[PDB]
Image (cartoon, rainbow over all chains, first blue to last red; front, side, top):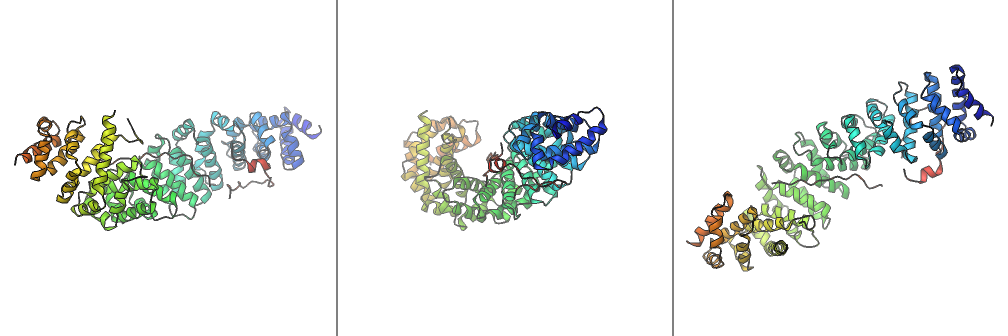
Length: 507
Length: 40
């Protein structure tokens, strides 16, 4: 009723000299508690502060006004006043200020609003705050960058449109540069959090990966800050499925294999997940992983994981990738046995294991079975019976009809038959397989419409048919009719195996 | 062929706050409620 009303009138004065002088006193009063609260309680005052800030051409006035809002932003009533008085649009404009002071007041004020004022997120987005904040990432004050990147994290979290705007603005590039450039923990952390939120968007992934984000994030994997390390891993894992074709992952792969020995569950989980994706169809990555003891490191991880399928599934998939299609694939198949992985691998075929893990494990065993030295061990561990069980159970759900556990029982069918197909290259294994009354099922599978099933069914039958007894049993099971038809399949494998079974049955 | 595992973890386990900017202003304590209540 004394200073406030008067200063308010002065702020709205037509003469700038009077305005500027008022801005200084107002700012001064905002530094004292009693008068700060008085200012935030005057709608007309706050409104005059905001208008003056976004209209004045006096750097000193712009500093005192922004400084005033900054001081008011420490209280709920201040934050509310700023919000209701068109504060957001004004503050966003100030982010274009060439003055550091003004810029710092503005970003701090906006940050406080985004953190504690409901409705601020939308307002900032609406005012085009995302674009300016991203444009400010080329500044060099690390504390400033930390607050700015934190604003982006708040605005992008769970909001797809904000994520795309950050992308269109050149966000990925700028954020990766931060990771590759500074050492200030708080900035690296907040920045890794923005990249994490952006890595969830399938459209942001390419931009981040091409900018060298995998390497930039890889750089901090051994930092003392656990929150920094973990956020980099979450991000790297989200990106991994989009970086399977990237060159130069050798350094990262070494670190990742080392991280598999971490005591931190979240670290190991991400290390395994990233490794599985990076070893997907990339012979170079597979070789590098084998080179640094990846096989042993993964076997140890699986054993340590126990029933934690978040770890075993990606670790088992990695091992599956590593035991196939590359120079060291066979040595890898052999090494799994040497590092005592066969027992646990077979164990994973049983409960509490869920289908996703079951499918990956069957795949790995199919690969391991390619190494003759694993035949006896796998048999000794009870692989065959269980593989048959999964096949029977899976085959039934197929005919009695889709995704179960997120897995199609048709995949289990050819996966198990495919595994039994290879294990059947061993005499003793053939005795066990036939001893389980499987032939009738295999012959049945020849009628499947899925060529892959046909092929693996014809395959096991062919291996089995090398023994006279089994051959006559197959023949006696009525395999001749279906095989004669598959003999004419345009599928090389189907026709070849089919002819082979027929030939064997007539020796 | 090898298969990809599609990860998209955005919300991360919650588990020193950001250091204030260097400005010529008196330190001001933020409303108690703004420090005991999570972000909006």
